Amino acid sequence: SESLLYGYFLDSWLDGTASEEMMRVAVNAGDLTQEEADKIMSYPWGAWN
Amino acid sequence: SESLLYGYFLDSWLDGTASEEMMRVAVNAGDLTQEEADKIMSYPWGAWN
Amino acid sequence: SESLLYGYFLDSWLDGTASEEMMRVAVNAGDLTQEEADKIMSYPWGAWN
Amino acid sequence: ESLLYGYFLDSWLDGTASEEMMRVAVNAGDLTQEEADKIMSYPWGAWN
Amino acid sequence: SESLLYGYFLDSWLDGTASEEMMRVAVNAGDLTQEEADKIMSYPWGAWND
Amino acid sequence: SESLLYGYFLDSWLDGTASEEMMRVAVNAGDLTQEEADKIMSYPWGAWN
């Protein structure tokens, strides 16, 4: 049920490599659900940068 | 059985990148249970350094 | 389900290491389906940089 | 075998983990005492 | 199904660390099938060196 | 089909970090079988250099 790349995209958001645009591209591609993208974006951007 | 990101968050607690505030964000997102966050926080913060 | 190297090739595209010619080689090798190569290339190349 | 066996073995081999840390891991339930003793049978910091 | 170290050896070929010498060792050891070694070698050797 | 740490020890042998001694300690601990240790040692040590 959880997307295979959830951890991958969460980590990219945490290190500030992924932008809001790239999270939307992932949702469009079906690599994340909108709910997962929203969950990831609730974390602080680049907190592990 | 344990959350997929348990090891991921334990490692960031041990390396001193994750704070208690980050642990709260992870629990709120549903990426850790409160019990797992409490377990992680029983380890010495920044021990690896 | 998904090809084992989907994440591996997506990451290489995102970090700008993989080119469209490399994606063709991966499809030819059978390590990606054409659908997965098309999905990866829809992401914007090099976006991690 | 505990999920973090490999993770703690690696930390012992690169010399980041101490015996005190291995005890904290066992107390947390992330390693069994048997696994902690197995890890400690390896040379500490060998990877260096 | 797929050998566990397929991705590992493909990455070593792309980064130029592996040559057919390594591919032969892995096949002999049973860490790769000949078909997988052949698939890996169809990629450009050392393409991801940098 | 094989020990969980097979790949981990093979990579350490190929990286040149692991020695023959280390491989025998892994067999002793039961983290590698003697067959796996022998298989790993058939590879060129430190090849990734």
Image: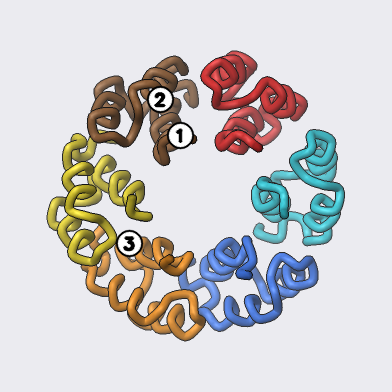
Chain colours: A blue, B orange, C cyan, D yellow, E red, F brown
- Image quadrant where residue C27 sits: top right
Q: Is mark 1 on a helix, strand or loop?
A: loop
Which circle, 3 or 1, is nearer the viewer? 1
Q: Residue furthest front?
A: F1
Residue E49 visible in this rendered orientation of the protein: no
Amino acid type shown at disc 3: Asp
| Sequence order check, earlier mark of 1 and 2 | 1
Does residue A13 appear left or right of residue B45 in this picture?
right
Residue at 74 percent across and 44 percent down: it is: C18
Q: Name the residue under label 2.
A: F36
Amino acid type shown at disc 2: Glu
Alpha-carbon span between mark 3 and mark 2: 32 Å
Asked if the residue under mark 2 is in contact with the one under mark 1, i.e. CB atoms within 8 Å, the reply is yes
Residue A33, percent from left and from top: 70, 75
Amino acid type shown at disc 1: Glu
Tag 3 subunit:
B
Question: Foreground: B8 or E30?
Answer: E30
- Image quadrant where residue A16 sits: bottom right
Determine which of the numbered discs, if any, sits on residue B15 in the image: 3
Residue E28, percent from left and from top: 56, 15
Residue at 22 percent across and 39 percent down: it is: D45
For the residue carrying disc 1, how many other residues have a C-alpha within 10 Å: few (<14), some (14-19), or many (20+)? Answer: few
